[PDB]
Image 1 (tube, rainbow, N blue to C red):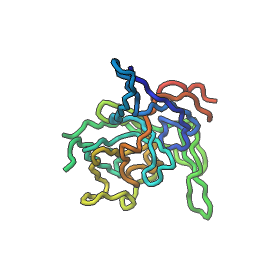
Image 2 (cartoon, rainbow, N blue to C red):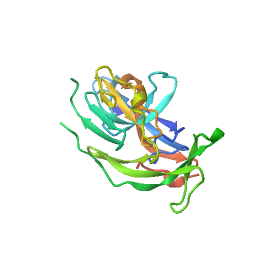
Image 3 (tube, one colour):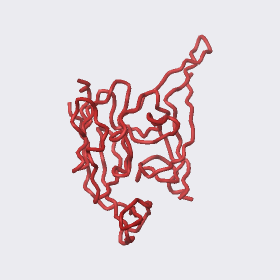
Amino acid sequence: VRSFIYEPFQIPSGSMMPTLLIGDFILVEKFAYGIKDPIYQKTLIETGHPKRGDIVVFKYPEDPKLDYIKRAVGLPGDKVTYDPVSKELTIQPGCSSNALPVTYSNVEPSDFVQTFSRRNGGEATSGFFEVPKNETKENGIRLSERKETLGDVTHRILTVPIAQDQVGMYYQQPGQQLATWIVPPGQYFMMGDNRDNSADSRYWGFVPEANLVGRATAIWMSFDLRLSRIGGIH
């Protein structure tokens, strides 16, 4: 006697590359589901919770009028530390006041190249393009790829070899060094797979449970007419 609500979701940005791409249309399963008991035919309202590594759609805390999609990397109580040089995560569960095994595969060239306009000789991102590994684009940088295993979940991330986060721009948590955060009760730390192209928890803080919409379950369609991407999230 249980029911789940599902809603389609268009992928607007490349913050989740290479896992999710601009043009992807995904299925999202709401955390809040109905529980129709037995004796009575009522519909109890129970809410599920994201597991570490889940790809989650949520309402932007600063402006809940917009929905974002990131990977839930930090759970309540998690002590999250990000090394901007190695671009690696360290996660220590239950440190609200034991190190989780987070491993990374070897850096390899990805299928994408990020380009940038050059008005005035400066640089501004101008898009992502799938480019054969033996080719290049002028004013573009080949992005690197590797696998991140957050405990039991393994997924891919992209990195921009010429970039490095400016720690001073991070959301700084009271009483904490820059680049370290303790996830508050009932809140989450969100990060996108395209690690140098993601305005996430590093910059605007945690996501309250109530802002959560649902978990991404599949790519129902994608229009960069990529029938090849329909299926599970990889």
